[PDB]
Image (cartoon, grey):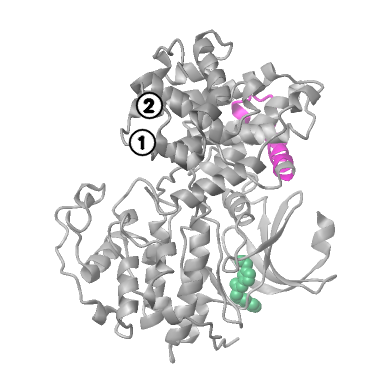
Amino acid sequence: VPDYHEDIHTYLREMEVKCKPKVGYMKKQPDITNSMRAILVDWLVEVGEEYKLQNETLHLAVNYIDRFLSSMSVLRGKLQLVGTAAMLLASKFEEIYPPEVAEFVYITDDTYTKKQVLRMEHLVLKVLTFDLAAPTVNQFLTQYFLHQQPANCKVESLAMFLGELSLIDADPYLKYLPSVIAGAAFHLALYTVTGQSWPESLIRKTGYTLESLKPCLMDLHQTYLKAPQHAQQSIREKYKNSKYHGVSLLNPPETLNL
Amino acid sequence: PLVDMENFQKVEKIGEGTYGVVYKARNKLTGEVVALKKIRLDTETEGVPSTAIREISLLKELNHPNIVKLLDVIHTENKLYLVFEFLHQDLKKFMDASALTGIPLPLIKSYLFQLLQGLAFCHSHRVLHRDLKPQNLLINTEGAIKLADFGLARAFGVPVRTYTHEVVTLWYRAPEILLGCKYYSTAVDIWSLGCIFAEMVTRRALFPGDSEIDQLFRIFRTLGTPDEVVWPGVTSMPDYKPSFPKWARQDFSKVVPPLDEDGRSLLSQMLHYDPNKRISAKAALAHPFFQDVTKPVPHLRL
Ligand SMILES: O=C(Cc1ccc2ccccc2c1)Nc1cc(C2CC2)n[nH]1
């Protein structure tokens, strides 16, 4: 356990409240829908797999996209340009060496130009006012894992899996803070793999009781159950790999007995 | 955008660099003196550089007296300007100018104290500096010192992976990095600080390596080649070699002669081999070495 472990969690909790996008922004977009967003994010996951990007990169990009769309009306044919720019910026921020812009233009099947991508980068930066270091579910899970005596790789992969799935559906995850989604994912994964529950140490650390996580937990469990039937499958595929101990193949418990 | 740039009068060039150029400038309307870092965006047509992305996004989150203030950001069609508060000198030039007389111990103590405060703030805000060296530390006539140059900085809400290219200049590079560890930790910034502390005190770089292997040997020759007992796991690290010479640890009173018991104690804790055991900026601030810290003003030969 680090020396600034606590100060950092406290600060992350403070910042997550600030980089929070508008929950009801999609209803106010005249041309795009949740499904279109779902399709975009699913696509970003593939891009991330194609260029072997960190998972954190994926989460930042989604955060950039949801904040951008919370104040800028975007048309169908431009949604992907916004997401491409968001992935480019996220890569620059998180990756050791991001793919060149040309690669991002390529993965769009030349739908846009190097020029359009760089201009959208500028606009996104302006709209977000260069505040790119946002807290993600990934970051909270990381902090949470240090509070796991029985360090279990299967538990971690699965929590990561459930955290990643929440990115796909604005409804109902947009209304939950990253620390809460992480909490639910952590418990659900721990429960499914070891039968253990939200640990006392994290209750003290986060102030979240199993009770407070219930609303999100019930939703995450539902997403888990329906996971195989979902229109978007890039994440399940990704988590079949041995790198993640094939946790997307694990069967979700029937009930949570909360 | 270009309206703001018109309000600045260029005074003189402060420094160069890859990212671009830094000029001392003056706000024509307010009279405020600043440092303008100009970045050309047509020298790669790769968009905004990753370094700017990070320095800007991380720096605007760090507001502390011992961290350089980013006042503004102006993004034109092909140019990116970062506006910083202005400080009279950087630690490297000052150390250079203090060669004959040396920097008074009270001022050295004051500077370390302030540097640890700035660093503690960075770390408690999940930011790793990663490039602490005399050149990146700014000082003014009042006796304050501030961390600057956050181009290589990184948020570690999620572990930061090691990169061959993006690394501290050799002389201040932590041993874990030289031995090829997987992830960075706050410990690498503390190590750099210890090296600077020693350099200020003795008037000579502590570990002036010529190469990576030579850097490691310089460190081993002074602090002793580390073993499993001193640093659990060291022999298993990627670049560790069982053929490494086995040097004995040099007596600290001979490495930094002008230092007293407290100074020697603090320095050795900052240079502890095991990164998990290396003292933190926070705990260093509580060390009895700073029992009598004050805030002297330097003799700046401007
Ligand atoms: O970097 C210096 C010291 C310096 C160095 C060289 C000079 C040459 C001429 C005039 C003033 C000069 C001042 N100061 C400074 C740099 C900055 C921001 C870029 C970080 N703010 N203040």
Inspect the image, locate mark 1, and give the three-letter code of the amino acid beneath it: Gln
- Residue B83: % across, % down: 70, 63
Give the chain of mark 2.
A
Residue B159 to residue B143: above or below: above
Q: Quadrant of residue A44?
A: top right
B263 relative position to B17: left or right: left
Residue identifier under label 2: A155
Part of the protein shown in magenta: A105-126
Q: Residue at x 38, y 71 (%)?
A: B287
Q: Is residue B199 magenta?
A: no
Give the chain of mark 1.
A
Inspect the image, locate mark 2, and give the three-letter code of the amino acid beneath it: Val
- Residue B267: % across, % down: 33, 72
Ligand 1 positioned in quadrant: bottom right
Q: Quadrant of residue B6?
A: bottom right
**Mark linked to residue A237:** none
- Assess disc 2: are there few (<14), some (14-19) or many (≥20) residues with their C-alpha within 10 Å of its C-alpha: many
Residue identifier under label 1: A148
- Pick the residue in front: B117 or B247: B117
Residue B41 to residue B290: above or below: above
